[PDB]
Image 1 (tube, chains in turn green, cyan):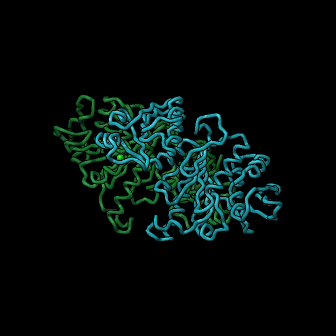
Image 2: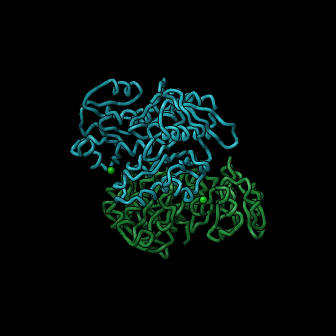
Image 3: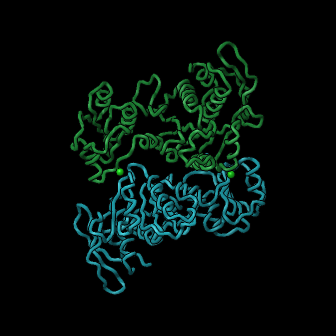
Length: 305
Length: 305
Ligand SMILES: [Cl-]
Ligand SMILES: [Cl-]
């Protein structure tokens, strides 16, 4: 048993991480300047809450988690550093949660948010109530449960995030590879591409890499990936393909072709080929997980945008 | 359920990995040019064995493992590449085994082999029959069991190995950081040091980093490690220390000081302060794991060299 202490536990990105850790059985304490409904919920769920910051609040903690909104002058942080207690940024602890669950990491420069939401929507339609991470915020749509209760954790994997390479997913998507975040990698696109290869090799040999081969950079690195892979796209050589794209209103329809399955007609309330591709990525993951066609259809059409 | 196929399964570094995978419940097949006692043992334990190489041998495999002794012209490898089956080097699969066990990774430029052996010796004295990896070879001293049966996997972690950063240990030792393998890191020692920091951050936040602070480079990076750490050495500021070093024959005696424990007198059949330090590293790990003083004393004195 360990105690994790959160400095600023009421912050929007912190409260969700504390709740997941509570759900996993850890002792959780936290400090914040103001009591709120967020801190009362955490206390109801087993968190010890302190109001105001003082060195005593950090006593007994085996780890501190600190936001990007805390000075090092903060007495709790300073006490932990003096006693050699580890202090970890919010984002590393967030990435760490995937080690306890069946982690689905949605990587790619664009489309992570939509693809993660579609995945959550489909899993929920299949009765699975996943916890999912968008913009650093843990969520579980309509759940009557603590965050992290599901077996599944679906998270955006941002290549500009310092913890990108410490994610340990079971399944990983790569929607596309753009140059937006070259600065994270010394302004070198080739280094940025190599990071995506290393990220996919954090998968276990039984894992699954879900690769958009309509993106030329994803297609380029594909031969480098020594893990099971399923490819998707409109490309005629993709494993999972969309054909017969059409509109009926603000709703996009298309037919998805999958290995050893009959063609499946789906719709989504979102325009553009990039959202057809995001739907394909979702369909691959859901198919790999054994989710029925009926939940896939329901999950895709029910998502709004 | 997955099937792993080993090309050259009788090779010395391959047979042990196949046995561990069998113990974990996977289907395992393998090909080799010659039947031997190694391949008959694997067959007795559930492996399907083929003699000679041909593309048919790789059928149904979800992954191939290939030695560094196989041409790409090898028909089994070629068949797998055509069908998009993942082909992984022996060393990556070996590192992967740590994900299924309580992994203890013994890193550092020098002293990995001795320290790993001492750890195994002490754990065995405590009745724990660990599997351990030295020189790429899986071993379990005097075990009446399949490799990998123990909860514990103790392995050398070599910084020149391509899989160094894909190890997922629960505990990690760093004996020292030397410049021997700078070439692996573009001939830059500072890059080599940064890799050791990244390696220790593969630990979980509940993990343990065991750090020799007698090495100036290990002491330098220590403030960077945001994980629980225990330090050891002759330095007076080390958490776990050796004092009163003395000889009686070819046997080295010393007293180990540990936080909140009485001083403990130990001996080892090996000369030099580097083997006192390797013993300290062992004592820290064994103490953290709850192993008794009597097994620690027995494990250290029983090891020969
Ligand atoms: Cl491959
Ligand atoms: Cl720290």
